[PDB]
Image: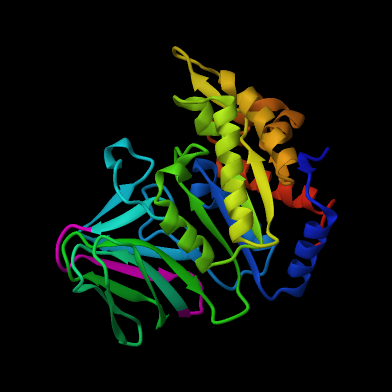
Amino acid sequence: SSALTSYVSKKDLKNLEKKLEKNQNIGIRIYGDSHMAADFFPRVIRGYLIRSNSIGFAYPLQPKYQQNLNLVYSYKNFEILNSRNPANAGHNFPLGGIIAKAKTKGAKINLDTTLDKKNFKIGFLFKAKQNTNAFSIKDAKNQSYELRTTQINKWSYKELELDLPLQISALQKDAELGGYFITNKDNNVFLDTIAINGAKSDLWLSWNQTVVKKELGLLHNDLIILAYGSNDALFKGFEKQKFKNNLKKWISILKTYNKNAVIMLISPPTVVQKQGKNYKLAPDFFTIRKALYEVAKEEKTLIFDMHQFMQDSGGKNKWIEQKLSLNDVHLTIKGYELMAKKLLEDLKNIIDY
């Protein structure tokens, strides 16, 4: 039984179905929380839905316990600011809400790809307190560049053709990096992720909206996946109408800034909450699930229901015993891949690839 429900017009589905057939330009993006931020579910979609040849957007540094398997990072003397963190509130956050801030002059980040191909156009988002040079870039072919803002305390962008691996050196203390856009000169097929452990569906409201819109336009996506809900059920501040109204605002922005894109909601797995010494179901999870179906119908999206597949195959307790799921809300790698393979299966009922 399919856990995938479609409210998308046959036109947008047919358009996406032939994009995948032509294997030329296919940009996929997954927004979400911990169920996506370690790339376990995304890696399966990236490996089997498309023939990935590019990277797309990536954080300036991965937060702890997060990764994008297309890239490898190391760094010295940088601080990671995270929009999900209350301690980091009030900062001017870009898309994704991750900032790599230099603690000292000469702070460094080394960046490489796990792909065998090394030459890319790399767009850098950066910010500085002074209009002098902010960062120096040195790539594998010993090309040396500089990132320099024209207005201070303002997110700025610059694209360079570079060969990975590269080294980024801070030329100012407190200079900030906000992310990379790593693409080919043409015919880009990629699946990138903008996921944050513990993020609620409305984390995007925390970011600088004009910077977000600029970065949405820097790279077009043909299929956009929003996988939220678990943390809405676990933390303060849930109200059904605010939940829907914010999500529909975000979907509308995404459709407007990504013309003809298909949107997929992913409703969370069974969400459980620590009550006393045990884990019990979260009261709002059922409400969140219903609202997500309502937003999918209202906004003409697909919706993949992780809870429905879990329930249709024995329930969370069966998934715990078989180490497809842990006892809290998190699944294991084996569980996320099974989820991703299930979605690929259900996807064949509406589109071919």
Question: What's the magenta region?
Answer: 102-120
**For this view, does 334 lie left or right of residue 86?**
right
Is 349 in front, or is 18? Answer: 18
Q: Position of residue 278 (x, y in %)?
A: 49, 15
Is 231 in front, or is 39? Answer: 231
- Name the residue: 42% across, 72% down: 123
Q: How many marks?
A: 0
Above-or-below relation of 159 to 130? below
Q: From this viewpoint, is residue 306 visible?
A: yes
114 drawn magenta: yes
- Name the residue: 55% across, 72% down: 54
Residue positioned most to the top: 276
| Rendered image quadrant of residue 228 | top right
Above-or-below relation of 331 to 193? above
**For this view, does 204 lie left or right of residue 144?**
right
**For this view, does 88 lie left or right of residue 207?**
left
173 drawn magenta: no
Q: Position of residue 180 (x, y in %)?
A: 42, 66
Above-or-below relation of 24 to 241? below
Is 293 in front, or is 139? Answer: 293
Is 13 in front, or is 66? Answer: 13
Q: Position of residue 193 (x, y in %)?
A: 52, 55
Q: From this viewpoint, is residue 331 visible?
A: no
| Rendered image quadrant of residue 281 | top right
Q: Quadrant of the N terminus?
A: top right
